[PDB]
Structure formats: C-alpha cells, structure tokens
Image 1 (cartoon, rainbow, N blue to C red):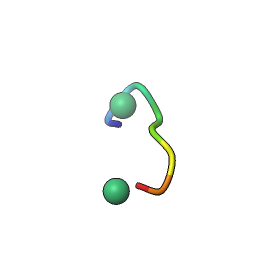
Image 2: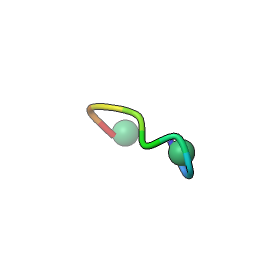
Image 3: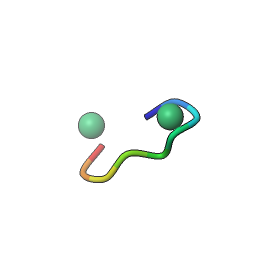
Image 4: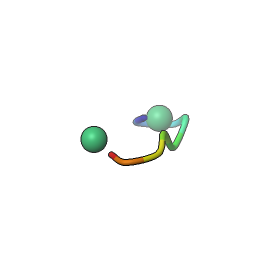
Length: 9
Ligand SMILES: [Cu+2]
Ligand SMILES: [N]
C-alpha cells in the first residue's frame, strides 16, 4: 500500500 503496492489505491 505504501511499500506493498496494493491494488485500487
Ligand atoms: Cu505499500
Ligand atoms: N487507495
């Protein structure tokens, strides 16, 4: 999300 590049930010 900040380093786990999550989808649909
Ligand atoms: Cu991340
Ligand atoms: N997001």
